[PDB]
Image (cartoon, rainbow over all chains, first blue to last red; front, side, top):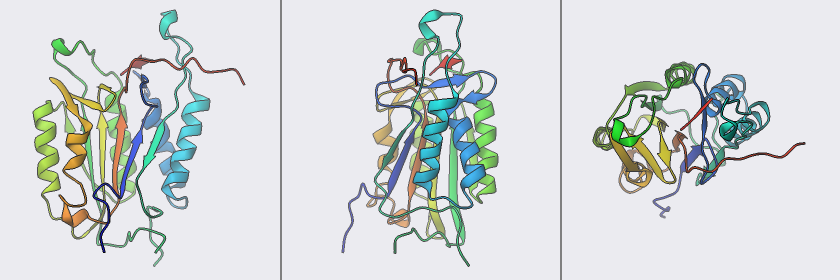
Length: 95
Length: 141
Length: 4
């Protein structure tokens, strides 16, 4: 007859706890670039957690930092999906 | 009963907080490229039928105020809620143009007991911001 | 590429 007050929240973090997150001055952040791309391609079919999983793979595999400063060069990133959701989420409805 | 009800009259709001310019004291440099993110998100969620509202360079006080006000709206006819935060950050923290705000303070306004018109509905917070100063050096595959 |  009741549900947790923390239920039904989904926090799609661009990076893992304790880590930097990368942003390209010309193309935008790796995470947002990937999120929008996966939503555009799969929101008409896939459940949200599965779309976010593809975002994780895209960010993890297609991006690597490039910097003249060796300290910021060749770095990688993995997003972090935090779900307190209680049901599957689809951005469409079947009439 | 395995899927959230998404056939309400409106998909819901998509609040985008786009912070690019910060006060010197923060030591944070201009977030070049964030406008590209904001535009991309606006179009992406517009296509998903979300009522997008973009806000630029908000102080930490303004972020809290915006969040409070939005949480006090009547979301009865909305299927869900989306908030996108684009800024500098630290673990558990998002930056207003003038300083840090605990993410918990922002999300608390939407708790199942504090925003009744959203109880039982998906509340999504998309966060593009650092969560510390560690680098992932990766591993060759 | 810049950080955040």
